[PDB]
Amino acid sequence: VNKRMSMVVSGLTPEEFMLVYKFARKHHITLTNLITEETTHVVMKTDAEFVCERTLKYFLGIAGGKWVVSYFWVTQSIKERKMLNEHDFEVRGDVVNGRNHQGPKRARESQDRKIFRGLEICCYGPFTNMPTDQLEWMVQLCGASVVKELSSFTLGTGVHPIVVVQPDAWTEDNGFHAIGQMCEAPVVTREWVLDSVALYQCQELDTYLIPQIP
Amino acid sequence: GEYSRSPTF
């Protein structure tokens, strides 16, 4: 048996989804609303130069080295009544990290050398607009080791511990500045992960570091 | 009816 096509779409209005659903129906393509290991294609809404917004399905698509292509692949197939090749429609960048950083392409080409290789990452809550277990899954797909609690860090010279938090999500407390007192590990924002994934290249922590209290 | 927009970052 061979792997089969399984799609999720992102950034589309319902009406656009319905057009794809009719599309998926005609050419017997599997189409789900939730992305899994079995999902092979991620279809993003882009501009004429194949630049999209950064969504959860966008990040997870890259993390899994899956094919991330533009919505224009569907509309063009309609226009010419054929099934043209998706690869021609791979998104080249996004509105945050660059219009032609070739992240998704590079992501496919480096699964033997994943960007978070040799790292132990703890996603220290809370989080907004992105479930914790999905973010944990994200770094897993990128070769990182997920750590549930701060005390669970491996102690060793070879281990590289990292604490990732989202300052926006904290509303009741200013607690993220005190984490350095509880453990021996760098503390950086969620944006470190997002940028690293989008470019599929491990960014320097310097700019993403969150100031601590000694 | 309502369309929760997909969360964008």
Image (cartoon, rainbow, N blue to C red):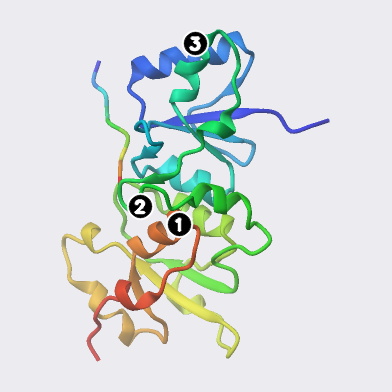
Q: Nearer the viewer, residue A162 or A98?
A: A98
Quadrant location of residue A186? bottom left
Residue A136 location (% of width, % of height): 49, 57
Q: How many other residues sit within 10 Å of disc 1, few (<14), some (14-19) or many (≥20)?
A: many
Question: Label 1 vs label 2: CA separation?
Answer: 9 Å
Amino acid type for the residue under numbered disc 2:
Gly
Of the two numbered discs 1 and 2 in the rendering, the one whose residue sits closer to the viewer: 2
Instruction: Identify the chain of the residue marked 2, using the numbered disc in the image.
Output: A
In which quadrant will I find the N terminus of chain A?
top right
Using the image as rendered, state which of residue A34 and residue A175 is in the foreground: A34
Q: Is residue A89 above or below residue A206?
A: above
Q: Are marks 1 and 3 on the same chain?
A: yes
Q: Circle 2 sits in a helix, a strand or a loop, which is it?
A: loop
Q: Which mark is residue A98?
A: 2
Pointers 1 and 2 within a single chain: yes
Residue A42 position within the rendered picture, expressed as x and y whole percent measured from the top left = 51, 35
- Residue A202 in the image, given as x and y percentages of width and height: 48, 67
